[PDB]
Image (cartoon, rainbow, N blue to C red; front, side, top):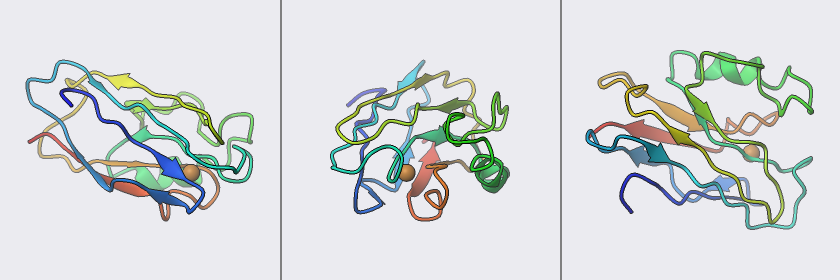
Length: 128
Ligand SMILES: [Cu+2]
């Protein structure tokens, strides 16, 4: 796929990919989240967070702090250029970011913020 990537997350708390390379001429990427599973968004939710590793943890720890209604996300985090809604069982959400937001050289990680999710589910983004 050009300047889009068909991601997913599942009941077996695993991401179907653990890395993403974005195209330097991509002038707008997309990440279409897809939940194939039987667990609700309240006990096995997932979401795609775009943010370096220099702040991944904090967006995490400060993510599971923002209630459950605040999609276990700190409201208006600058430490996230892009993120997806908290879908769940049979749900499907996405997000498209500015590839001018994506700085070269700087490492980058996507993950899940649901209390103890980022730990397991994640993967490296890059600007090849
Ligand atoms: Cu998750």
